[PDB]
Image (cartoon, rainbow, N blue to C red):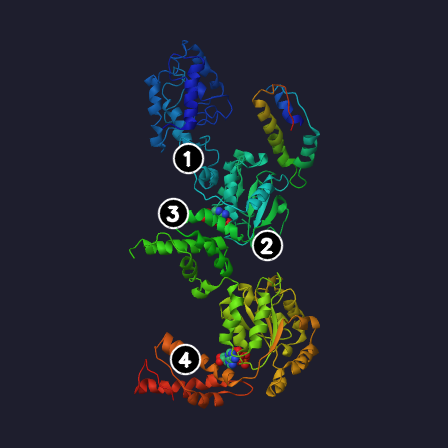
């Protein structure tokens, strides 16, 4: 088919011969139709490949209607009734230069091109159209690749940079390519409002990448074809330069600044995370010409670098920082894109899963912007069993809630059944039963600690502050294990509980738990700075220097601490724990098997001694760790037994285990030590029990998969 | 203001003009940038005005020599 732009003239050329109602369509006709007026809006005048190629049309503007008025007049129906194959060939004849100048359809040049024989003054004095001489000449001048489609704007190739690498997604939008977006409709509007703001049209999108900052621009691009775009912003469309620079190869990027200036702010530009010193500096001389609406974006990072220098190029720029979208955001796009990426993968899904995805995803996402990771996990979930579907065995092209959440998301870390059974409420109600499994006896620590974090859970935690604890007893009482149990129970992670020594990391460790940089600023940061979920083990806190206890109270208070870069980071996901062993003295009361509030007063007295009441009053619960009953002693057995079977009977040998209190009293009695508990017995068992087998292993008289107690 | 009108009413646009203080204020207030100047407004003077009102007029229903300011 002919080019619309061409055909726009062509039918108007048929219209041309119609206005004077010409008898026939004949070579010199469209010489008028090619031209509304001498304006380059009519390229055939000046911007024509001929005026630049051979024949300038200035005075040669004179003759065109001179013929079409001197055509013998006709009546309406015979007007444009005939191609008059002398002219009618130009229909086909226009397809000749699409060869030598490499085009496909029939364009403004081509419709022009065919005419190059008789469409003219052809005489002894011939003001005419040179055949190959003007076009193949200047059809590179014009354009240099003309051909795209019958559709499209003027085919004068004003800007080669805009036609080359400038991507119009509004095209793609009416082409239906991109996926519609949601919920930045605030930012969408506001940034477009910024765009609609005459003062600062340019926004600065701020935030960490992967969040949808150009997904913003997606619906923005859509609002262009959705035509919500403001009057100020109507005539403009989307260009977004994804910079591929590949003599200066950049000035192209600078030359296009005219090509848009050609369009005269008929578009908008959007650059995403590349905002930096360019050549030289990026952008402005076109913007700095006062012109050029652009959609700016960045992480605070690139915002921290060059635009900090001037700030009066940001005089165009309202900085808008995106936040990681809410659940419904994920949900709704999922709601929109669940059918998408299940049809992208040709499968089906439970929306039950879909929302449930975001749940743990948002919860345990260590890094990314959730919908991505979600859509990742989704596509992961999708493709994963879809790949399981398309490859034999598959039965479910739909996919479940659970595994599609858990088993899929289990490829972050794992522990699905615990990722399963928890309603995020199920912890507390079931915790002190669960906690009863780990730390033996200690019903105080069972209730008190948990119930106090049941206050830091239940949703009753402050928007910023964790639960707070200071504990006395054996170190080895299951104290750490408690907070490991906490770390294990609460966060399903053993990494959560972190060794933090108040004692030795103490005074100028205020520099070494973080440092305004004069790389972690110090220990405490990227522990949590990576992972806001954590469990804090603060070692013998009263042995710390008071230098930190202020910012330690600043940990207690407000649950956040100014970092080395100064950031004040959320610890309230955690539970602040303090440690004191000084009651080992006061375990004298526990030696007398007192109710320890006998000395817990003195304990409270002892701790109230050294510290700010603030620093003191933060503690939710202080729990003395009670005297070990034989149970409390000998229930530590299965702990060992567990960490026995974890390897032999589990992760290596598949060897069964049995003991008797005979041997266990031959253990625990010795196995228990007063001050250190059975922490001795652990590294005791390491041979005479263990290596007794490591003996018997190759001694082999009795073999694997057996058990014999001594 | 003077430059465009003297391009056109002379020959092209035959154009009699109107000014809201809006534009009168706008162009001065809004159109002029402190830092980047009315230099863009110089282009904008087209846009919100010439581009706008010609577009208003180019239909011709608002006739030649007529004017409508925003
Ligand atoms: N609300 C949404 N609706 C539809 N698709 C979305 C939405 N948010 C993100 N996407 C999808 O995310 C992908 C691209 O996301 P996008 O690039 O916008 O994130 P980003 O934060 O802008 O990364 P960058 O900051 O480097 O531009 C596309 O596949 C797009 O369809
Ligand atoms: N009631 C109990 N509950 C849980 N673990 C207990 C209990 N009594 C003794 N233990 C033992 O405590 C061990 C770990 O103690 P924990 O780590 O809590 O103290 P710790 O502070 O780390 O020891 P330390 O700090 O002195 O090196 C476990 O391996 C377990 O066998």
First along the sequence among labels 3 and 1: 1
Q: How far apart are marks 1 and 2 (CA)?
A: 41 Å
Picture residue at 59% right of the left edge, 25% below the top: B56
Q: Distance between the residues labelled 3 and 1?
A: 41 Å
**Label 4: chain letter:** A
- For residue A343, the mark is 3
Mark 1 or 4, closer to the camera:
4
Residue, disc 2: A304
Mark 4 neighbour class, 10 Å CA radius: few under 14, some 14 to 19, many 20 or more: some
Residue, disc 4: A644
In contact (CB < 8 Å): disc 3 and disc 1: no
Q: Do the residues at pointers 1 and 2 share their chain?
A: yes
First along the sequence among labels 1 and 4: 1
**Label 3: chain letter:** A
Q: Is residue A554 left or right of residue A128?
A: right
| Disc 2 within 8 angstroms of ligand 1 (CB) | no
**Label 1: chain letter:** A
């Amino acid at each position: 088919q002919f080019t619309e732009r061409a055909l726009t003239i062509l039918t108007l050329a048929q219209k041309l011969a119609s206005d004077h109602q010409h008898p026939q369509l004949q070579p010199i006709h469209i010489l008028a139709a090619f031209i509304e007026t001498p304006e380059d809006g009519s390229v055939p005048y000046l911007q024509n490949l001929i005026e630049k190629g051979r024949y300038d049309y200035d005075l040669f503007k004179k003759v065109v209607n001179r013929n079409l008025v001197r055509i013998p007049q006709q009546q309406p129906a015979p007007a444009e009734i005939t191609p008059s194959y002398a002219l009618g060939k130009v229909l086909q004849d226009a397809a000749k230069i699409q060869k030598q100048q490499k085009d496909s359809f029939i364009a403004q040049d081509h419709i022009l091109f065919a005419l190059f024989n008789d469409s003219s003054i052809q005489q002894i004095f011939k003001e005419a159209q040179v055949d190959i001489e003007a076009i193949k000449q200047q059809a590179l001048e014009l354009r240099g690749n003309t051909r795209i489609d019958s559709r499209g704007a003027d085919t004068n190739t004003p800007l080669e940079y805009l036609s080359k690498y400038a991507i119009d997604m509004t095209e793609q939008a009416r082409q239906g390519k991109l996926d519609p977006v949601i919920g930045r409709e605030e930012e969408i509007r506001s940034t477009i409002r910024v765009l609609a703001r005459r003062i600062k049209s340019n926004p600065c999108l701020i935030g960490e990448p992967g969040i949808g900052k150009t997904a913003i621009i997606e619906g923005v691009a859509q609002r262009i074809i959705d035509d919500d775009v403001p009057t100020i912003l109507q005539g403009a469309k989307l260009f977004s330069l994804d910079l591929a620079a590949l003599g200066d190869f950049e000035e192209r990027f600078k030359g296009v600044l005219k090509e848009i200036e050609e369009s005269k702010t008929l578009i908008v530009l959007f650059i995403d995370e590349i905002h930096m010193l360019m050549a030289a500096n990026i952008l402005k001389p076109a913007l700095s010409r006062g012109q050029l609406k652009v959609i700016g974006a960045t992480t605070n990072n690139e915002y921290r670098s060059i635009v900090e220098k001037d700030g009066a190029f940001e005089r165009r720029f309202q900085k808008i920082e995106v936040a990681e979208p809410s659940v419904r955001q994920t949900v709704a796009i999922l709601r929109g894109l669940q059918p998408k990426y299940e049809i992208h993968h040709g499968v089906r899904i439970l929306d039950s899963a879909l929302v449930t995805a975001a749940q743990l995803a948002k919860r345990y996402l260590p890094y990314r912007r959730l919908p991505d990771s979600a859509l990742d996990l989704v596509d992961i979930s999708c493709a994963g069993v879809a790949v399981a579907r398309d490859s034999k065995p598959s039965m479910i092209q739909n996919v479940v809630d659970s595994d599609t959440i858990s088993e899929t998301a289990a490829r972050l870390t794992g522990i699905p059944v615990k990722k399963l059974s928890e309603s995020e409420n199920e912890k507390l109600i079931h915790m002190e039963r669960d906690l009863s499994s780990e730390v033996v006896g200690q019903m105080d620590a069972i209730k008190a600690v948990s119930n106090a974090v049941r206050l830091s859970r239940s949703g009753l935690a402050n928007p910023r502050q964790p639960a707070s604890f200071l504990f006395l007893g054996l170190s080895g009482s299951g104290k750490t294990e408690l907070a490991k149990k906490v770390a294990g129970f609460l966060f399903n992670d053993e990494d959560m509980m972190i060794r933090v020594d108040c004692s030795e990391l103490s005074e100028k460790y205020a520099v070494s738990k973080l440092l305004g940089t004069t790389d972690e600023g110090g220990f405490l940061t990227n522990q949590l700075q990576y992972k806001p979920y954590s469990v804090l083990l603060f070692d013998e806190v009263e042995k710390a220097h008071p230098d930190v206890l202020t910012v330690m109270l600043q940990m207690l208070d407000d649950g956040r601490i100014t970092s080395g870069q100064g950031k004040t980071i959320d610890c309230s996901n955690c539970i602040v724990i303090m440690t004191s062993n000084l009651g080992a003295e006061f375990i004298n009361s526990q030696q007398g098997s007192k109710i320890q509030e006998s000395t817990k007063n003195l304990v409270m007295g002892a701790v109230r001694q050294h510290f700010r009441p603030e620093f003191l009053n933060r503690i939710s619960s202080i729990v003395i760790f009670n005297k070990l009953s034989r149970k409390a002693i000998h229930k530590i057995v299965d702990i060992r037994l567990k960490e026995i079977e974890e390897r032999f009977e589990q992760n290596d040998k598949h060897y069964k285990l049995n003991l008797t209190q005979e041997a266990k009293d031959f253990l625990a009695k010795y196995g228990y030590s007063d001050d250190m508990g059975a922490r001795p017995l652990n590294r005791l068992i390491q041979n005479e029990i263990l290596n007794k087998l490591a003996l018997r292993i190759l001694k082999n008289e009795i073999k694997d998969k057996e058990t014999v107690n001594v």
